[PDB]
Structures are given as structure tokens and as C-alpha cells.
Amino acid sequence: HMAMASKEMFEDTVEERVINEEYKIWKKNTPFLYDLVMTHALQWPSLTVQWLPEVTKPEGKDYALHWLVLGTHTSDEQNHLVVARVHIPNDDVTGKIECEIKINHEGEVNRARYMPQNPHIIATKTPSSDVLVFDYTKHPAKPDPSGECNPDLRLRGHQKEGYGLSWNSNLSGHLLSASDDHTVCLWDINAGPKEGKIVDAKAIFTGHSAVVEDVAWHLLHESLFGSVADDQKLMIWDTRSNTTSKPSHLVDAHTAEVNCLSFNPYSEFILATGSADKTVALWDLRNLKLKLHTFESHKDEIFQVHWSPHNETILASSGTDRRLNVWDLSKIGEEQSAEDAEDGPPELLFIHGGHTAKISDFSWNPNEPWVICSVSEDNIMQIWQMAENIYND
Amino acid sequence: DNIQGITKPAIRRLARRG
Ligand SMILES: [As]
Image (cartoon, rainbow over all chains, first blue to last red; front, side, top):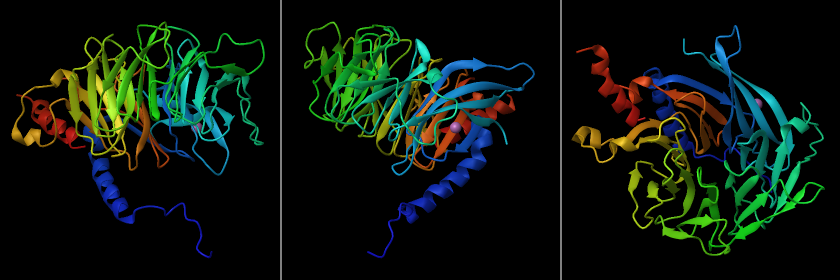
């Protein structure tokens, strides 16, 4: 009645102190651990990040241009889908971030992903039911303050919101989406009618019995895709199969809810999975029954997992423990001393401790090896790169 | 031996402790 609503705080003042002191120590250690570390505080936290595939080294400049696809998270005010332009300094204060474009968006951006075949086409997941599609070359350079959201395409099929989003790298226009409605929708944005901005799901997969958390196309076989849900099950589907309620394979992947999955860009067989049981599981398509390996070290739920686009044996995972772990499969099962075994398994390459809140997403840079961008719930975004000294002898 | 070889195990340990 008298007391105000406080969206800060709103924090745990005890945990805050611990987090901050661990951050101070991390910061003075950065010169040892990183060849590059850049930080920026966004006005609103971003739940999503993805590098655009374009890079350029402008003549006469001592840096390189890179682009990020970001989003906004406000429940009170106007949301935007944003493409940021960044200067990453040449290896031979530091750095710069700017806005290439900013697009009026209804509700927060749960996830934003670009179409590999046409990088200026971007799909987004809304707090509503529709997933949206924007062509950013057809939107004004600066957004209208009125806040009107005019997506180039609205895709219908879901009853609730979601996060899982995946373009097909081999089938242009084919998009997958996961949702809290227990389903996984499929669209072909090339077909539909002549007008206007509304297309229907081509398929609605109902194999799951709970909130399906993530979805991903196979990077090599254009008809296979994986799904992951709160029923603790990893399912693998086939599009040319005429049954949308029973997958080709069904796996009891974790003891808790499964949050994310990522196919290896080099091996057509292996797959990784992140769960609420604080572990990442390795999977091979030949035999799903056998869980190849289990990555232990995360102290809390894992929400994102991504393979390196340069090194086939490199894996990264982030979660609620505010840490981003980098794994090297080539060091699995390898022997180690007792003092080293106390820090974690041999495949644990690197623990990124620059974030002071949950990491919502991260993205491997496709043009600069070992460069990553991660975003946390406390408005921070970090573009960083592990010290060469650590991965290369 | 060289000095990098001396600080390689130290840095790699620091990396796995965050
Ligand atoms: As920006």
C-alpha cells in the first residue's frame, strides 16, 4: 500500500558481495588469461547474441568491423531487434560498439537468428505466440519512436512463447521453432500465399509431453533435426517421415530437464546436450543408447551449448552459475595429478568468469578463431578471446 | 627450458579455476 515496487533490489545483497569480490580477482587476472577482453553495458539486457557472418578490415584502420545480432529485454518499455557494429582491434577505451540498425519489436526478443542463405533475414521469438521474420533492408535506418512493430512475416502455429529457433543451412527458408506449448513448428517462408505477412506451420511435432526448450537442424543432412524438452528427453526427427508425434529416435538424456542442444559442424554424427542436472552430454547418431561422455564442472543449470566453428574438438557451454566453460574433447580420459584433478576433469580447457549474472546466450565468432561474445542478465555483453598460450602449445 | 614453458602450467591452471 505504501511500500514501492522495487525491481532493484530485488537482489541478494549477500550473494552480490561474493560475486563482486570474485570479479575483482578475475579482472586483475585478465592479462594472463585473455588476448582480448572487451565489455559493454547495454541499456537493457539481451537474451540473445549471434555474430553476422560478414567481416571486413577497412583500409587505413587498425581494427576490423564485425556485426552482432542482439535483442532487448524490457517488460515496461519499447523493445528492439538490434544489429550492432563493433571494431575489434587488430592483434598487431579499446574497441567500439555502434548501432547498424534498430528495429521496433513487440515484447522482448527471446531469441534472434539469421538465415544462413540471406543474413539480412532474421527470425525472432516473441513473448507472444507468433515467431516473427524481419528483412532489415526493408526497415528504416532509425526506428519510429511510436514503437509500431511491422514484421515482414508472422508465422503461426504455436499457442505459447518459446526460445528454440533454427534455420536450415541446407534448405533455404525452412525454420524450426520450439515452445512452451509442448510442440515444435516448421515453416517454409518461401511458399505460402502471395499476400501478405502471414504463413502457417507446415508441420507441428508433438512428440514431447512437456515444455520443449530447444530445436536444431542437422548441419549436413537436410531432413534431420533434434529437439529437447523438460520431459528429460532428446528426440531426433525426420521431415520426410509422415508422422509428427513419434521421432526416429528417443533418448532419456538427463536426470533433469534438457535446455539446449548443438550439432558438431565437422562430425556428421556427434551432438552435445545441456541440462538442468549441471552436465553436458556427448551423443553419437550411430548409437543413441550410449551416452558417450559427461562434462562436469558447472555449478548450476546449463542453458546454452555451442561448438567451435574452427576447431572440431572444442565445445563451450554457459548457464546460471554465471560461468562459460570451454571443453577440449581431445583431452578426455587423459591422466592428471591430484592438484589438477581438484580443479576439474582433463577436458576442461577454460572457465570464463567475466560475467556477474546468469549468461543468457553466447556466440562463437565465425571469422576470428577463439573470439566469443557472451551476454548476461545484468545488461553486460563481453567480446573476449582466450590467451593463445592456453590452447596452442 | 624456456620461461613460457614455466608459466604454461601455471596459466593453464589459472584458466581452469577461472
Ligand atoms: As547497439
